[PDB]
Figure 1 (cartoon, chains in turn orange, purple):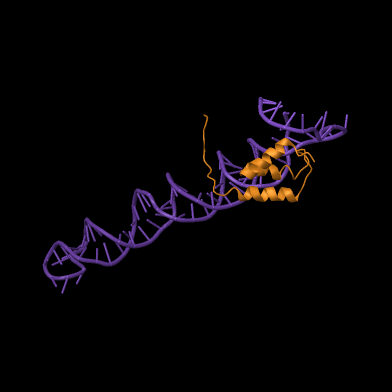
Figure 2 (cartoon, chains in turn brown, blue):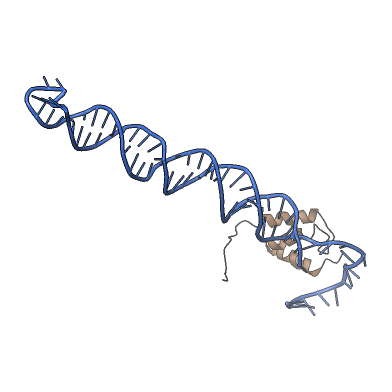
Amino acid sequence: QNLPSRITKLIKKSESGDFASSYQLYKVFGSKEYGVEPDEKMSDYFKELSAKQLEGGQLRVADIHL
DNA sequence: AGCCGCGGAACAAACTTTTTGATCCGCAACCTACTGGATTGCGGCTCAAAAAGTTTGTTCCGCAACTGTAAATGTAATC
């Protein structure tokens, strides 16, 4: 069905393990705007994986510009 | 490029919890025996009054995603 190359890159990133890679994967498969047909089950899987991969991370302030 | 409801805020009258400045009243002191005058004085206790501390009803401030005819595009990478 010729999944776009950017979609394949995001899937590879999610397989490696990232939280945004699956965020922008359950919002790419849940709407028609991003350019791919909406699949609900395979978007729900990406949403669950994105939420599961958030644990263990620390939120810190990196830089600042006054 | 426009500006939805939501929730803090910047202000501003009302409650509300103490800071202060007298007034009083036992209360031991004199004085002498003891209500000694026709006396003072002195320290807890209480009084509203008012300069301080919340509490609560109103008014603007800000901000997001996308809009009405409208692209599925073999590979990688740029703004």
